[PDB]
Amino acid sequence: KTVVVTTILESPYVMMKKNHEMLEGNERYEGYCVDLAAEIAKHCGFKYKLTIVGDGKYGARDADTKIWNGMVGELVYGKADIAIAPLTITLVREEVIDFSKPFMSLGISIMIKKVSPIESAEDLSKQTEIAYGTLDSGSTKEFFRRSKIAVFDKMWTYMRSAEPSVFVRTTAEGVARVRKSKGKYAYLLESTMNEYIEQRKPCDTMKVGGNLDSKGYGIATPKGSSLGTPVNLAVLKLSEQGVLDKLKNKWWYDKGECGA
Amino acid sequence: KTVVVTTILESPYVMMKKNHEMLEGNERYEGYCVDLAAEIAKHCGFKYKLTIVGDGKYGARDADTKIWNGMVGELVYGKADIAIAPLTITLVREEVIDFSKPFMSLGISIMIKKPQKSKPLTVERMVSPIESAEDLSKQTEIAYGTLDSGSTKEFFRRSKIAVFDKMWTYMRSAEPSVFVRTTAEGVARVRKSKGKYAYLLESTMNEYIEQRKPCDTMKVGGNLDSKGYGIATPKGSSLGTPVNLAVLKLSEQGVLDKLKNKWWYDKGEC
Amino acid sequence: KTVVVTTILESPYVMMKKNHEMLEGNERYEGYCVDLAAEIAKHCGFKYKLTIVGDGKYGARDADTKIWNGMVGELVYGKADIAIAPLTITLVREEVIDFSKPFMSLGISIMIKKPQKSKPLTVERMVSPIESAEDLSKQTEIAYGTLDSGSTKEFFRRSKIAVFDKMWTYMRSAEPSVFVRTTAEGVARVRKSKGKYAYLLESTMNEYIEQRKPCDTMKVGGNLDSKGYGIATPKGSSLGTPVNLAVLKLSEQGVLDKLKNKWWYDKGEC
Amino acid sequence: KTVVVTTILESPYVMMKKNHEMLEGNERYEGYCVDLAAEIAKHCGFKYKLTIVGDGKYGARDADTKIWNGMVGELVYGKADIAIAPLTITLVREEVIDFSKPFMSLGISIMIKKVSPIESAEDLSKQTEIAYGTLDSGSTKEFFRRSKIAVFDKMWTYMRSAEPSVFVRTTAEGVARVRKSKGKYAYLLESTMNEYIEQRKPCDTMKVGGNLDSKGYGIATPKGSSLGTPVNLAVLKLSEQGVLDKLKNKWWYDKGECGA
Ligand SMILES: NS(=O)(=O)c1cc2c(cc1Cl)N[C@H]([C@H]1C[C@H]3C=C[C@@H]1C3)NS2(=O)=O
Ligand SMILES: NS(=O)(=O)c1cc2c(cc1Cl)N[C@H]([C@H]1C[C@H]3C=C[C@@H]1C3)NS2(=O)=O
Ligand SMILES: NS(=O)(=O)c1cc2c(cc1Cl)N[C@H]([C@H]1C[C@H]3C=C[C@@H]1C3)NS2(=O)=O
Ligand SMILES: NS(=O)(=O)c1cc2c(cc1Cl)N[C@H]([C@H]1C[C@H]3C=C[C@@H]1C3)NS2(=O)=O
Ligand SMILES: N[C@@H](CCC(=O)O)C(=O)O
Ligand SMILES: N[C@@H](CCC(=O)O)C(=O)O
Ligand SMILES: N[C@@H](CCC(=O)O)C(=O)O
Ligand SMILES: N[C@@H](CCC(=O)O)C(=O)O
């Protein structure tokens, strides 16, 4: 029985190679998550087929409709069997799907154009001269929406009431927007994605400040699935063997096409 | 029914209060884990009594006897119901007990006695004999060790990495023994060995000791790996899901990071 | 019964909200004084309706008619029951209305257009033509004025200090009139007067304007005197004691200090 | 009829005259408060006699005894008619006596012995290497005791549980204690007394940071007394005339027996 693996087009997590038009199956995808899925399948011992979620959303709830979209929706409604992807482990997600132990630590970070005038999140919030926004239908937006801290609350309130729309459909779109904003826009994204962008050409983006919070990426399975325990044990074994560190080094630092 | 919360004695997680002679119950102990347990109790309604393991070990399964000891050991055999303590999530432990999502990230770090400031126009520069784990492995004039019956020793024993395998080979055949019974024992050994002993311990305790007087220890290099502390729970228990959800709530609500900051960096003696 | 809260339109104390075209009631206005009124209502339980004076004046005695105008005027004759605004506690007002303890301290300050940073090794130094009120009085090239029907004008009118008497004598016989109807009008006059006009206003408004864009104004010299803003109340009203106790309680809590911080410096720039 | 004025021996508010042994009546006292009392009496038009309170306390409530001591106790129980003294206006005091409008602004300030490693009160609360305390039965101890802010709460908790006693009987005693502590003790007093001490000989003390809060000194009168309105109007007239500023300049800066 083949296992359907939902995943998102994210760099360096999943990429469609460079000449994928002549390739078929799992061979036309590459990245951190492809290698992670291969290792998970090898440890557990199942055949898998990589598929990209039709709509490029990580997962959220609609406007009072109680409908999950993205990979989380693909998992809840039985369309997918597992999700090897940069899926953040959150409260609202864990109540509907089973997350494994985190395989990558991360955090919310600010990326701007190339001493920074904002640095910390407080100075970014206080100064309205530079705009800041998050990915739409993601987990950082839901972090700010549910946040009760005064700085985070005020940042969220500014973000929701912004003219024009400060959110972005894709993190690539957000990176492009901060690139062509001439330093007038800031992007709130995961620290791993921020580092990957800042170590890639043409290196006009840099990360300021620290991490707003600490989270992790998990492998998600449908609630009450027989694969949850095996994939959790596989993640634990890979972490103890240093395979996750090797994969992160390979897809984040080994190539390094930037001057640093 | 009041369930028990087994826990190790470790600063800044659990420390006896100064006026604990006349105190009893969950007010004798203070630290990060005591109010972590308080927050867990607030989130999911139950009464809890803090306990300390008699043998004073985190937990490891003895070879040729297949018997778990320490916090994990007495959690497995039903003498405990939940273990809120700096317990590392490991594969061997996850097969006998249920773990929650990590509430604190950590890594294996190196502790050495802080060397004297080198002097040469007149600037004071920091010079150390060890800067990573590879130079620790290759060199032989400085001994190094870990905590017995802990996760660090088990990580070194089951390591196929060449440098870690070499370091474990040195550790196993060492005279006198380089392993210590308690973290405080390792810190005292480092402080008294005059730079001839390095202590391999978790990064959180390493930073906590570094920030406190007499601040004669320094942490060299980066973390050897990436792990986390989880709230342990007996296998097939009903507390696993509420504990997981409470950990997620505390993480997303800023309780965890503010607790870590006010137990680690607010009291910066040095 | 709903008690009405008369108030002047002054920033950062009271500002019309951006989406106040559709908003109605107490939600139309925002600022320091609306927060103060909310806290006062929280302390002593009452419903309050914010009201802006039609006259647009703080209040004074008109010439030869012995009639009060502005907030003080409409409070004396019963069109309002409490005044929560930057109203200055003065002797001439305390004889006709009841004042509470000052919720914010203030002084009379000098506002001039910020000069250009003088360039002479290659250091940039601030140079100003006026450094105190004495040199403002002795000099004649720069005009200066106050706000009409306000506390500053009455203070200069009834001053027996030689320098202040000289300044008042210049003010009374100035041509064209140096008195402005609104604080914003005086600030605009200073801004567009190319350094030929100086505005004498309360230190709080001076600092707030100095900290906000385009921030081309500067406050020269120290405060001319020491006064405070109180919450006004008609003589014999039963609200005097509860409002006084509320002011003292809010001062003790630090609510006043945090309101000042979040309405004066947190929102500032440049 | 004569009016009994209660006051405390405080510099530069009330001092014993240099040749007071041969002096009688109000002529043997001098300071800011003596001049203030003279001006208040001249404005209102009453005869007064300065009396120093037998117990050298400003006023507070005892341990669950509901008994007022010091000047506030002298006023509540009818032993005095008015109090021209550095009496801080507080909620607990205002409920039992009538305070006039403040005639002097002040605040809580930290004074130590002459790199400034203490700076603000936050670092004082964070570091226990240096000790700090307040005046016993004053208005600073009651401010810290009733404070709900975390920094002030922890400062008060440290101060109450101090071995040996950290509080001082008199402000002069606290000045001496910080003088002879060789920079190991800090004193929390009013900003006016702090300034007067810091510009006086031998100038070995200095004030750090800023004011912890904003308060004022008022003229206190028994509840429901015919003198409250006249003395309030007198204070307002003196402030509008600049007399209070002249008195503060004369007793704080005119002498100036230090190099500054
Ligand atoms: N250095 S890293 O981001 O590639 C990284 C991050 C992490 C790893 C392993 C690696 Cl290599 N394992 C941990 C897991 C292992 C066991 C302890 C915590 C979880 C369960 N999660 S983690 O702390 O998110
Ligand atoms: N900054 S820290 O070490 O105190 C820390 C570390 C971690 C926290 C929260 C904090 Cl405050 N929560 C995460 C958890 C939250 C959700 C995402 C990963 C796990 C599930 N684990 S963690 O990455 O080990
Ligand atoms: N820092 S400030 O100007 O906003 C400010 C100023 C003042 C405050 C409170 C604040 Cl926050 N309260 C005092 C009052 C409290 C008690 C002591 C003096 C009066 C009665 N008046 S004040 O000295 O005019
Ligand atoms: N500069 S000072 O400390 O001598 C000083 C301080 C103050 C003065 C007058 C002087 Cl001279 N008057 C005010 C009073 C006057 C009217 C306005 C506020 C009160 C009622 N109180 S104050 O703000 O506490
Ligand atoms: N990893 C995030 C992506 C969205 C974001 O960057 O906030 C998620 O799974 O929701
Ligand atoms: N926390 C570790 C023990 C500490 C250490 O080994 O340094 C464990 O769970 O075993
Ligand atoms: N607050 C002053 C008016 C402002 C001013 O005169 O500058 C008053 O009560 O009259
Ligand atoms: N001025 C204070 C006394 C000094 C102090 O408490 O610091 C009072 O009236 O209570």
Image (spheres, coloured by chain):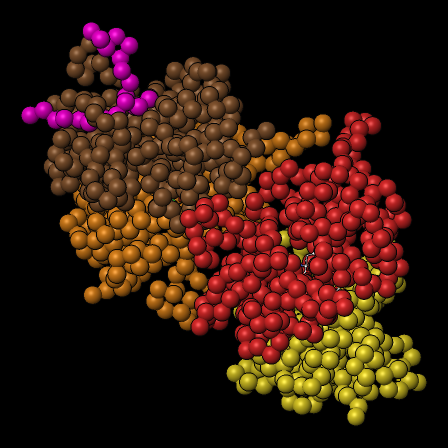
Chain colours: A yellow, B red, C orange, D brown
Q: Residue at x 53, y 29 (%)?
A: C129
Residue D20: say if magenta.
yes
Q: Which residues are magenta?
A: D1-22
Give residue D116's position: percent from left, percent from top.
56, 30
Q: Is residue D33 above or below residue B177?
A: above
Asked whether D21 falls inside the magenta stretch, the response is yes
Can you tell which quarter of the image residue D8 is in? top left
- Observer-nearest of A73 and A205: A73
User: Farthest front residue?
Assistant: B65
Residue D139 horizontal side relative to residue A8, left or right: left
- Quarter of the image for the N terminus of chain C: give it: bottom left
Residue, x 71% and y 84% (percent of image)?
Answer: A227
- Foreground of the two, D155 or C206: D155
Tally of numbered tags: 0
Where residue C109 sits: x, y (%)?
Answer: 42, 36
User: In x, y percent, where is residue A119?
Assistant: 66, 52
Residue C52 position in % (x across, y down): 32, 58
Q: Can the viewer see residue C46 in this picture?
A: yes
In this orientation, which residue lies closer to the viewer: C221 or A226? A226
Q: Residue at x 41, y 55 (%)?
A: C31
Residue A22 lies left or right of residue C139; in this view the side is: right
Instruction: Tell me if I can see residue C105 in this picture.
Output: no
In front of the other: D178 or A139:
D178
* Residue at 56% across, 47% down: B266
